[PDB]
Length: 112
Length: 109
Image (cartoon, rainbow over all chains, first blue to last red; front, top):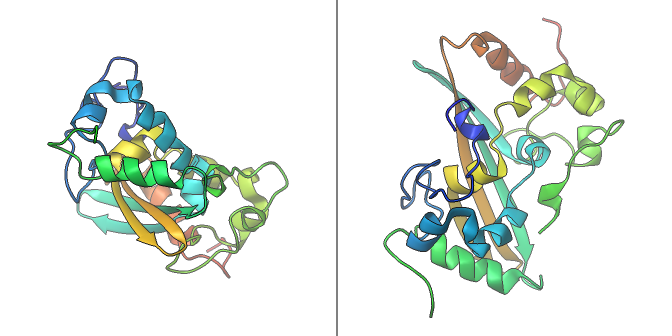
């Protein structure tokens, strides 16, 4: 909702991803989500799974590589945060399989 | 899956949670003052205004998975823009100038 900073927006019940965070892409901003995670938003249980891998505020600020870039329109501040899920993590397989599905997953749906 | 959910409680330095501050690498945010003071630094609080929420990081990011022998490396690249005419622009710019790759410096300048 529109009275929040874009970066602070959250996807409320019954909204599509695309929606709060724009259409799903490939190899750009907003590339996470297939056609079914887009439609179900927080309904999709793969979402709940995935948020376990999203940095907190603190982690995002202090655990990322942070790169400022000034441009005529202002300051673009990029946080690059990489979560490592160890190959022996009980949820490794699931996490890999979600990412599979949804990273650049526009135009596709799961179940195979 | 949990390092990434860490937060810095009161009395902790950044580097007692997120490792020593670096330059051009992971953990590059925070000068010696900010590292020392952790969440007590007034600049942190402002800077957290620019950090994506959970949902915005997942879905507003460019997300890139890489499998390596060690496991899955999930990278989120999220860019926040502060407009040149934002009342907070000059402030954000200065904090970034102090804190980005700021290890080994302190404010007052």
